[PDB]
Image 1 (cartoon, each protein chain N blue to C red):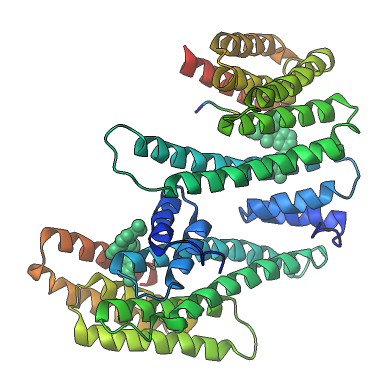
Image 2: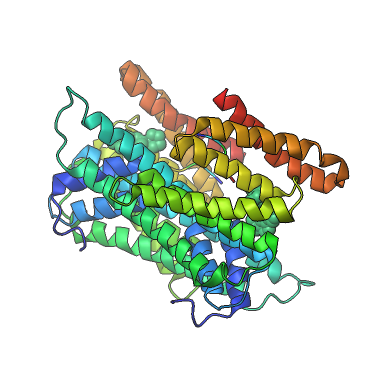
Length: 236
Length: 236
Length: 5
Length: 5
Ligand SMILES: N=C(N)c1cc(-c2cccc(NC(=O)C3(Oc4ccc(Cl)cc4)CCCC3)c2)cs1
Ligand SMILES: N=C(N)c1cc(-c2cccc(NC(=O)C3(Oc4ccc(Cl)cc4)CCCC3)c2)cs1
């Protein structure tokens, strides 16, 4: 690790600076270095890690979608042969995306998840594990595609089971997990009905628990609830 | 060069794909590979090169400015010592920026400028040379700062002299060169009066030549003329 | 695309 | 910042 010689606290400080500078590749590298110090992550540190890699892989996914769209058009009946270049470059971006996903999954497996005992950490990491297998699933086409999908499903399911036992229905981690698992059902698992049911039930159970919250907790929970509603509006 | 084994035409094709995917680091790498094939660049290819590196260095400059601002605040009277991390990370981004600038300047020196005989290519490359020395000047603080500034000035001046002899006053390359040389005067050379004079004279001479243009050439020229006016409005 | 966090 | 192209 090229960050092995830097202090943990300095890595966290520089991740925050990288965020302010919108340098998310740097942010992710700094947070990878911090994870590799071997200590558990605090709540803020977990979110720094997630924000960094979500931004990096989000950009890769957007680029992949553009290139995949161009590639599909090049393969329509009537197109002029473009040669191998569109496929090659889509494959290049795809391989870089898979590499980032494998890196994050590696951090979760070595050894963030196994040391995470509190619900807020364990559900958060298992959600990430489902998310990064979901991104692998988005580009998967080979002998392993069903297994990648099932790895995402299994991680999300363990996270769901813990969240329903250990967190209130308005907990923003629980809500964000349900939001993303619902998208998994709709976009990956070809289960739109499950996606819609999960989003609606999550929204309604949260609604009924808002009365217990402070003004600031209310703002956090209703923000994610609105994303659930947004998706439901998209899908119905 | 990691692009040495790829066909020139494939590099150009992939630069265009990278642009569509907003992958400007890739775009720049592809166009560096194309330059290193040793052939002169067409008009479209010159603009692909410039667009790529302008976007890469533009992001670095934005990040550097954020970090430099944080660093200056950390050094105000009353601040809590943050340790070396802000300076270190600003230096990291700065060094990466200098590396990109040196790469572009290297391509211009080996051997784009010396083979560029037509005004549209030679003025374009000398403008770039002024631009990338200007970006080096923005971060320079050492024994070499005056020399960096003078290297920018000298490149812009040679480009200006050629453009006034060989191009009409509405030529968009001539206009863009004058726009940027004017910013050099204002922001780098501490010569706001020269900056304002150059922008105004360029604008007025272009105005008087618009009558010679087609509708499409008019659109191109007036676009840059509006940027000259925008800067003049900022400065007066 | 649908919203995720 | 001022405009450049
Ligand atoms: N960016 C940083 N420097 C830091 C960010 C945080 C932080 C701590 C707690 C919650 C959030 N919430 C979030 O970011 C959003 O909501 C969720 C909800 C659920 C999940 Cl599982 C993930 C995100 C993401 C979309 C809107 C808010 C952020 C600490 S530091
Ligand atoms: N992006 C691509 N795939 C390609 C772009 C081009 C192309 C060819 C000729 C002119 C322009 N003009 C430009 O981009 C703007 O104007 C100038 C003007 C002067 C200078 Cl010196 C530089 C830019 C930049 C700001 C607005 C327009 C673009 C070909 S291909």
